[PDB]
Amino acid sequence: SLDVLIVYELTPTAEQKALATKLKLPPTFFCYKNRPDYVSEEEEDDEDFETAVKKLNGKLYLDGS
Amino acid sequence: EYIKLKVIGQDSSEIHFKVKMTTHLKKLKESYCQRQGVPMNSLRFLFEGQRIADNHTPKELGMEEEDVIEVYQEQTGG
Amino acid sequence: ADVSTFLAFPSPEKLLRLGPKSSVLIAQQTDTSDPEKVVSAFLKVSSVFKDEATVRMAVQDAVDALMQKAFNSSSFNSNTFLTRLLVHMGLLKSEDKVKAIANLYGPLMALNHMVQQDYFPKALAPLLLAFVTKPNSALESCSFARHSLLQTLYKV
Amino acid sequence: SGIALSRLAQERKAWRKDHPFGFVAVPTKNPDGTMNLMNWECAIPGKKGTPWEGGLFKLRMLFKDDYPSSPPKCKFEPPLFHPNVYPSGTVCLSILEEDKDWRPAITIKQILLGIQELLNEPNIQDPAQAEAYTIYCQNRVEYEKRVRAQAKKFAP
């Protein structure tokens, strides 16, 4: 009748999916770091909320970037 | 004929579909849900920011190739 | 000691059995401080309003006093009242579990009067008007009391 | 609970690496200098097009030991003017209610994103605050006018 075929579906690592499975998170969660661009395995979180809100300074809508 | 679409969910769940520009987008919608275990309603699909009709089709959206669709978990106020 | 027990288990009669000194024995023994308690009293008193001659006059004045008090002491948020009131009258969802009162007749009649008095903040006017017209089961099980209040309010 | 501190831990990292534009979700900190995961300080942007555009609305997010089993409580700081936001600033939303639309697979990115959509899709068919429900029904042109305002007042 009406053809619609699923050609591709983002899949994670065996260890990734299994981690998310432990955390009850959507299987495609740590795919953010599975990407090619900005990713590694080292960084220290500390920035203060207030700081961040300001770091954002410019408008809140990227429209026009 | 055939235009590959990118249905991007709201949890990094990406899915690619090849669809005939003569087929009702509902077919696409439905597929998603069952190939994801979620009732036809539970979600909601969007394009160009605006919602997507159940009878819609690129016949109306003029969706080229490489297009993108956003899916949002359905909710209501309280 | 009388008002106390009267508040525990209301009664269209027990109210009267307090002499003419009830219209203030209650409108004093009650913690007029915070809205929540005002709401509790107000409803309690109302829960025994009978279209009767002297009984509604007892109820009316009780409310007339209790409110005359609280509405006159800036140390009281009128809106917080109107709210917790609607919440107790099962007309608006609370952030907790409140026991919605059975019948809204007494209140809808007690309110019917209060809105007419002057000590009433003509500002909460539309907010009550809105939640009375608000389609609701019980606020329907008393067509009379409501249409009345609606009428009373349409004028205020 | 079960694996709260871990999932949460992860969601922070994930959030840093990737997250919607204009949104802020920075946890708080313990006296230990460490990081507090049971309490974040988020800030949702308005929504281009909607009358809610322009402003950035802060909201806290308290998680319980149980998470992700039970959803996170959410409060706007300060409280917002919106049909489905309690006076306390709590946001009542189907998705956020344990016994309704909440499912563990939902993440913070979603909630914040949801809540944002909610700003403009009020469910007046069931309000959580008299204040707004009234104005919404009473007059629409005003409800927007009130919004346009609240938005500017919270513009970065």
Image (cartoon, coloured by chain):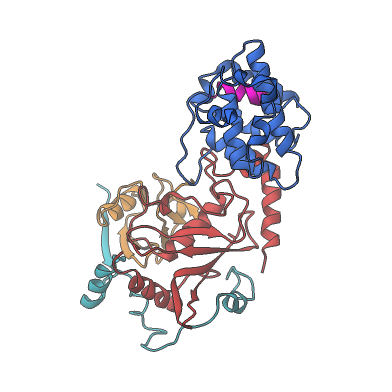
Q: Is residue D19 above or below residue D116?
A: below
Decide whether residue D80 is among the magenta residues. no
Q: Which residue is at 56% across, 20% downward?
A: C14
Farthest top residue? C53
- Left or right: where does residue D20 sit relative to residue B66? right
Residue C105 spot, x, y in % from top left:
56, 21
Farthest right residue? C118
Q: Which residues are magenta?
A: C104-112
Q: Colour of chain D?
A: red
- Left or right: where does residue C8 sit relative to residue B74? right
Residue D43 spot, x, y in % from top left:
56, 66
Residue D93 spot, x, y in % from top left:
46, 50
- Camera-side residue of A56 and C113: C113
Answer whether residue C149 is visible to the viewer in this image. Answer: no
- Camera-side residue of C117 and D144: C117
Q: Which residue is at 31% across, 66% downward?
A: A25
- Camera-side residue of C33 and C28: C28
Position of the N terminus of chain B, as image quadrant, is bottom left
**Chain shaded orange:** B
- Left or right: where does residue C26 sit relative to residue B69? right
Answer whether residue D19 is visible to the viewer in this image. Answer: yes
Q: Colour of chain C?
A: blue
Q: Colour of chain A?
A: cyan
